[PDB]
Image (cartoon, rainbow, N blue to C red):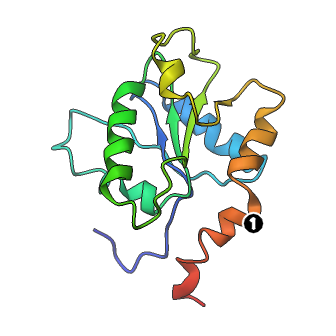
Amino acid sequence: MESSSEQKFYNFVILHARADEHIALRVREKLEALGVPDGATFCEDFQVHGRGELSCLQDAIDHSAFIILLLTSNFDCRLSLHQVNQAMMSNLTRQGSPDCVIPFLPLESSPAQLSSDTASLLSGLVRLDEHSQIFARKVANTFKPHRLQARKAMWRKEQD
């Protein structure tokens, strides 16, 4: 539902638990301090019916530039992988970018707190940190400015 609402669009979906809000909210901005905008954050709540929050996970895959998986001890990575995956293997002819994932790691949580499989789960993506002095180059690497635009240039087509 929306009353003549303006054009809203994200560049990435920050997947995190429900107790990792401020965490994500802390990233969105931190992202705006490097380049990528606030974007958003996809959290699953058992309070709602389910499809009362967002469309789907594969939506941010075709909508958001790169999906950001908040790999936190409070959040579920395995699932994210499953979903994100299905989304990818679901519609490849679209973006066919199975490497558009961004496993973020906040200070609140850590990778060591994750299973030994996680390493293999993100054994290809670009581990994004929030306490790394390189993370800046990591985000500016994946979420480049020429991409954030060239990626939204497909949505702006509306205004263009």
- Picture quadrant of residue 127: top right
Q: Amino acid at mark 1?
A: His
Whether residue 76 is visible to the viewer of this picture, yes or no, is: no
- Crowd tier of the residue under label 1, counting other residues whose Cα lies within 10 Å: few below 14, some 14–19, many 20 or above: few
At a point 38% along the width and 80% down the height, the residue shown is 4
- Picture quadrant of residue 11: bottom right
**Residue 135 in the image: x percent, y percent?**
76, 34
Q: Is residue 48 left or right of residue 129?
A: left
Residue identifier under label 1: 146
Q: Is residue 90 above or below residue 153?
A: above
At a point 23% along the width and 51% down the height, the residue shown is 52
Whether residue 130 is visible to the viewer of this picture, yes or no, is: yes
Q: Is residue 62 left or right of residue 55?
A: right
Of the pair 38 and 94, the residue shown nearer to us = 94
Q: Residue furthest right?
A: 133
At a point 74% along the width and 40% down the height, the residue shown is 138
Q: Is residue 44 above or below residue 36?
A: above
